[PDB]
Every structure is written in C-alpha cells, then in structure tokens.
Amino acid sequence: ESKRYGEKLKEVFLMLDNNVVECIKEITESSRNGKLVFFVGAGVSTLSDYPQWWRLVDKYHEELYGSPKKGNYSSDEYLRIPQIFYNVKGEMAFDGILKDFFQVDKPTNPIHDKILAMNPAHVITTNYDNLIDTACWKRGKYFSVISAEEDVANATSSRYLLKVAGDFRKGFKGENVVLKEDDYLNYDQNYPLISNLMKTIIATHTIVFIGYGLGDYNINMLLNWVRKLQKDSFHKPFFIRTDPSPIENETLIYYENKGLRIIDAASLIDSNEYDYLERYSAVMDLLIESQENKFITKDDEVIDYIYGKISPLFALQYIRKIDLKHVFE
Amino acid sequence: ESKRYGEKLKEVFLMLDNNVVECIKEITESSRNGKLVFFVGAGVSTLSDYPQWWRLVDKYHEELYGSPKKGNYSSDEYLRIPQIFYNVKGEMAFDGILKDFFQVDKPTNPIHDKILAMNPAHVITTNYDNLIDTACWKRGKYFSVISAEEDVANATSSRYLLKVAGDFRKGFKGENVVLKEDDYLNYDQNYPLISNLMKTIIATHTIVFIGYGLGDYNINMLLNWVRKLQKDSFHKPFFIRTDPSPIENETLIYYENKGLRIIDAASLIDSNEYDYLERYSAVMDLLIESQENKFITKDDEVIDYIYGKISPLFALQYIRKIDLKHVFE
Ligand SMILES: NC(=O)c1ccc[n+]([C@@H]2O[C@H](COP(=O)([O-])OP(=O)(O)OC[C@H]3O[C@@H](n4cnc5c(N)ncnc54)[C@H](O)[C@@H]3O)[C@@H](O)[C@H]2O)c1
Ligand SMILES: NC(=O)c1ccc[n+]([C@@H]2O[C@H](COP(=O)([O-])OP(=O)(O)OC[C@H]3O[C@@H](n4cnc5c(N)ncnc54)[C@H](O)[C@@H]3O)[C@@H](O)[C@H]2O)c1
C-alpha cells in the first residue's frame, strides 16, 4: 500500500506505450499552463453511491406497466419511458420520484479531489448532484456555478462550473434538468447560452473526459459537432476510459479518427471486474505524479527540466540568486 | 380455413370495438375515393423470408470483433456497427457483404396482393427489395418507381412508388441506400426532394402503416415532424400493429396522443407467438371484406348504402336502367 502503490505506479510508468506517455505529457503541460478543463459525467458521481439513471427508469417502467424490464435498457428506452410517464401519469408524479431518488446526501470520492488537484480552469459536468460543488467549496477553489440560462450573464468569478444538463438547486422538478426525450429534442432552443458557453471552452482549452462511457449521447453529439469544423483547428480531446474489459482495437481506431485521444484505464493495470475506484485512481495518480516529476530518471531528461527553465533567462545579463529559487519551484 | 374463415371474420367484425369499426369505415371510404396510401415497412418482406437487417449487423460484428454479440442489438448498434465496419474495413468490403446478403430472389407473399387490392393511390416503402415492384408489375398496376433524386423529375405516371430508403436497382452498393449512421444524419441533405414528396403525400392523402414496429426509428421521425404542424390540419395516420403480444394501455394512449390511430392485430384474434402471417391477414381481410359489403347486417345500413348511391341521381329527370347497373357496380 504505502510502498506497494508507490512502486507500482513508477513501474507502470516504464511500460506505457509512447502514445500514453505523449498524452500524459500534453495533459501535464496543459494543466501547468492553466488551460486544462475536465468534463465529469455519470461515473465520477456513482463512485459516491449516487443512484444511476436506469434505477429511475425502472421505477417509471414498473409504475407504468407493473414489472421491471427483462433485460438492460437501450439508449432509446432511457429517454422514452420517462417521457411516456410524463405524458400519461403527469408532471407532479414525475417529480415525486425525482424527489425520492435524488434527495439524498452522499460523500465525495477521492477522484473528486484529484480532479481539483490539477487546477482545472473550468469544470463541465453533465450530472445534477452537488458533489463536485461541495468538493470545490471545501477545498477552497471558488467556481461560479452555471446551471440555468439566467446564470450565464451573472457570473461573479472567472472560473466556471458549467452544468450543461440542468441542476436541482432551484428544486426537485423536471423543468430544471434534461431527462426526457423532448428535453433533448429542444436542448438547443431552451439552452442557447450554455451551448455556446460549452462549445467555446472546448475550442479554447484542453479537455479531459473522465467519468464517461464511449457510447454516450453527449460524446456522440460532441463528436458530431466536432466533425463540422475544418482541418485540425483545435486540440483533440483526451478520453479517460475506465471500463472493465480492455478496449478493442477496431473500436479504438474508429473513435481516434473522430477526435478522441483515448487513454484506457484497463490496460495500464490489472484489476477486478468491479474495482472502478482503482481504475480512475491509476490514471489520476499517474497524471498527478507525472506533474511532480517522480517519473523522471535519465541524463537527457535533467537537461530538459534544467534548460527548459534557464533558457528564457538568457536575455538578462545577470539574474539574482535570491530569486533563482523561483525560476525553479 | 376454406369455409370457416368467412364466418370467423364476420364474428370478429361483430365483436369489434367501436374505434376499430370507425377506423375501418374511414379506411374503406378513403380507398373508395382514391385517396389511400400505404406505408410499407420491413415486416412485409420478412413474410417472404427476406434477410432481416440484424443479420447484416451480426455479420459485420463477427467480421470486426471476431465473435457474435451477446444479446440483442439496440437502436445504436443498428447504425454504429455498420458505420464502424465501413470506416475500418472499407466501402468495398461493406458492399461485398451487402451483395452476398441481399442478392437473393424471394416470392411475393399474399399481403403484397391484399395491399394492392385496396387500390392505393401511392405506396411509400422503406425497404430496398423489389418485391413490391414485382407485385405491382404482375397485376397491371403501373407505379413510377422513385428511389433516387434524379427519379423525382423524370416521373411519367401519377401513381408513385416512393422508396424513401433507397434501392439496389443501380447496383448492390451502400451508396444507393441509407443503412449506416452517417447516412441517417445526412439524409435531409442527400435526399431533399424525396422527403418533400413523402411529406406532401402524407399531408394530402390517407396513410396506413403496415409492417412497422411502434418504436421504429422512421415512425418516430414522422411523429416528430407531424407535431411541428398546427392544429388538426390533416388526418391522423392509421397504424396496423401486428406484434405477438397485445398493446398495453399506457403505450396506446402515448402514441394516440401523438397523431396515430392504432389497429391492433393481436387484439382482434388469438394467434400463436410466431403466426405473423395470420395476424397480417386478420387485419388486411377485414378491410377488403368490408369493401365487399360482407358485413352489412341491418336495415339502417341497406337503406343507407342504396341511398348514398341513388341520392345524387335525384337531380336527373330520368336515368336509364343500364346506368343503375353502373351506379351500383
Ligand atoms: N443499462 C441497464 O439497463 C442496466 C441494467 C442493469 C444493470 N446495469 C448496471 O449499471 C452500471 C452502469 O451501466 P451503463 O449502461 O450506464 O454503462 P456505462 O459504461 O455507459 O456507464 C457509464 C460509466 O460509469 C463509470 N463508473 C464508475 N463507477 C461505476 C460503477 N460502480 N458502476 C458502473 N459504472 C461506473 C464507468 O466508467 C462507466 O463507463 C453497470 O454496472 C450495469 O451492470 C445497467
Ligand atoms: N429486437 C432486436 O434488437 C433483435 C436482435 C437480434 C435478433 N432479433 C430477431 O429478429 C426478429 C425481429 O427483430 P426486429 O429488429 O425486426 O424488431 P421487430 O420485432 O419490432 O420487427 C419489426 C416488425 O417486423 C414484423 N414482422 C412480420 N413478420 C415478422 C417475422 N417473421 N419476424 C419478425 N417480425 C416480423 C413485425 O410485425 C414488426 O412490427 C425478432 O423476432 C428476433 O428473433 C431481434
């Protein structure tokens, strides 16, 4: 643990392919320059035992028909069942179940802290829990929260916490979040400001995609928007994938040509089929410890961390030694 | 069968709900006025043993990932797996699978003839097989086939056969149909005239959906387009549903509020789990035998059928006896 984990991370750093090393090098540089923006989704919140969306679709399904579905719900059944419930049963009944499920208090997993350990310029989450807001407040990093159209102009600070999928701050109702099918069908007409505010950060910042699946609605919509741009014209987003099985090569080639630079979590380490907290932690600790220069051991590498900090100080003819402990950390 | 079927259909009609009776009467009136259009899907081709699309999505999966998938493909897999196989293995292999799977010759089931016996003014189909074209040709009905943009202007007849999903007439290649995921995204740009033609036919005619699942992709786009329209302004399409299990009440209310009048084939008879032909023929025979006046069993209907034919002739001073045999057929 104390020694095992420290040795394991440094050992895994030496076996990584050049692609993962380049991805980590770019992520660390973006974080140091101050242009790193995380994109948290469902998966960084379920580590805090937050309910998954299918557990509410099942409740809607068994309150409409009478029995849970015999299988896993598809992408259409995630938006169509709650819409059938809203149309048939009504709106107050649709909000009673939301109040029952989402009126819970849960802790903040360590990942929520690690995301704040890299100093992200912004944070773009597509979930409605206040776990990330609580973590940011407790760690002392003030972030202006933007969960409504009226919040875009009234931004007190410069760092954002854009919740592009609504929020339950104003109350536990379905008019503040995007859950049904018609909510997605009218997202660009009901949220015209948070769409621009999200598409601008993606184009003028480094983006990471922790906590997301590789076939989500949001990821595919973002890739559809990205394909409408020109030749390169922007930085390809990084995608931390933490699924149990290793990613197939065909599906990796298919997605790496659409913009993603995938960093699979179940390839640097071997873990159990349910140890998700130890798959997020591998990538996050790899990035954080790459920031701290722990994974630096070579003769030519010390002539880069030394030249890369002394070379700018060449126009000056004689710099003081009292502040020379500032050009280095 | 031979003689019991005539009594069984009459009993079913006598034991029908009033909504289905009204739907059948309106359908018969539309057929008699020449304003009936049939929307045929990929459920009248499987009666001819035509290869279902999930077999191609299974061959693509087997050739990509080496082994078949576990379970049943969702909506996204129906459009993404073919797209991944395209982007990875090339258009040549994509079309090689298409030619090997779709270059077959199947007969025309009795439903293709019951469809034509109702005398439709148009036929809109999302399948690519030429089964409906063969059925039209082998009965003396001339329909102008329309499966590409260049065919819209070069039409010669007034009765269209609008294949709104393409056709393999000009070669068994994937560029002549809509099968992938990017084909569906760029459909309004690649088929701007066929969409307008289909929308105009839907607006100015009576539509019956036969062969489509209720949660189909195509149906849920027409249902979204038909909501952007104003108040009533048109006629709600008829949907002939022939699934093995009866439709639930909530899902019936959900789709009847979206502008659909549903005729459930699994609620008018008692068929087996795989007796799809006996359910198609149970709803396509009620309409045809209602046209033939096999259900008139009251004096208020015999003094009305005669009156609807004879009343317009009251203007004429005297009609010949060889025209009374023309007024009635
Ligand atoms: N889809 C259904 O109807 C259904 C039915 C029964 C059970 N489940 C279970 O719900 C879980 C999520 O299913 P999904 O369809 O959203 O796949 P998903 O990959 O789209 O889930 C999103 C991401 O959540 C992340 N994550 C972090 N901790 C997790 C945890 N304990 N469990 C799951 N994900 C975690 C993962 O990185 C995952 O990629 C799965 O464990 C699944 O077995 C789903
Ligand atoms: N639903 C899936 O994703 C899936 C996946 C793998 C295999 N399958 C198999 O394919 C069959 C149909 O799958 P689908 O994707 O077309 O969904 P679906 O059942 O909704 O098919 C659409 C329509 O085909 C009509 N039809 C007429 N004859 C039919 C026949 N012999 N078999 C099936 N439908 C007939 C049905 O009335 C239906 O409305 C299923 O019975 C199953 O054995 C389905």
Image (cartoon, coloured by chain):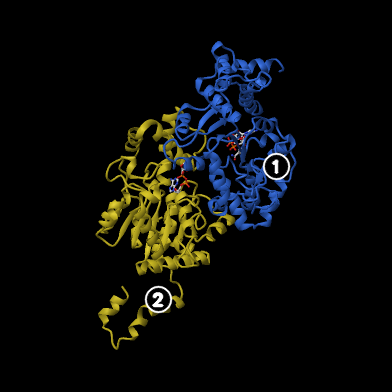
Chain colours: A blue, B yellow
Rendered image quadrant of residue B112: bottom left
- Find out if the beta carbon at label 2 lies less than 8 Å from the nearest ligand 2 atom: no
**Local SS, label 2:** helix
Amino acid at the residue labelled 1? Asn
The image position of residue B59, as x and y in percent, is 41, 33
Q: Which mark is residue B305?
A: 2
- Assign the C terminus of chain B to one quadrant of the image: bottom left
Chain to which the residue tagged by mark 2 belongs: B
Q: Is residue A242 visible?
A: no
The image position of residue A234, as x and y in percent, is 48, 36
Amino acid at the residue labelled 2? Tyr
- Assign the N terminus of chain B to one quadrant of the image: bottom left
Q: Is residue B306 visible?
A: yes
Position above or below: B71 against A307: below
Q: Which mark is residue A130?
A: 1
Q: Is residue B169 left or right of residue B274?
A: left
Rendered image quadrant of residue B66: top left
Q: Is residue B162 left or right of residue A319?
A: left
In the rendered image, the residue lying farthest to the top is A299
Q: Nearer the viewer, mark 2 or mark 1?
A: 1
Position above or below: A182 against A287: below
Q: Is residue B187 left or right of residue B171?
A: right
**Local SS, label 1:** loop
Image point (27%, 79%), residue name? B323
Image point (36%, 48%), residue name? B190
